[PDB]
Length: 31
Length: 31
Length: 31
Length: 31
Image (cartoon, rainbow over all chains, first blue to last red; front, side, top):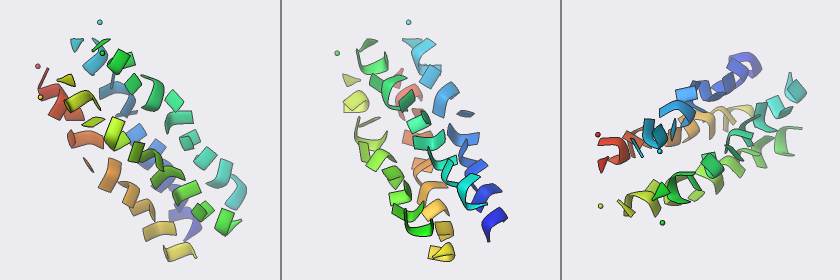
């Protein structure tokens, strides 16, 4: 179903936290 | 619902802007 | 709708090409 | 359809593995 889709999208909106913070890991190794 | 799914997908299509520009942050630190 | 959702998902499956190749930009600047 | 959407989302939840591990490629080149 639709609710077990919305509750994947809200896994992606975790991966796009852990995307951003583990880029900002790299950026704060570089400047 | 379907419209509150399409309006997550259009959050992901923000994260995949902030993905691209904060890679291009790193690429422009490196070359 | 459902088809104009599947045809966002197949934008994300472009961003997750341009994700991979513009990481592999950075990896090939580094090793 | 809905099942051929859930089975894109579970492609994205592969890309967000290959996201994480090919960042952690870069992080382990840098520290």
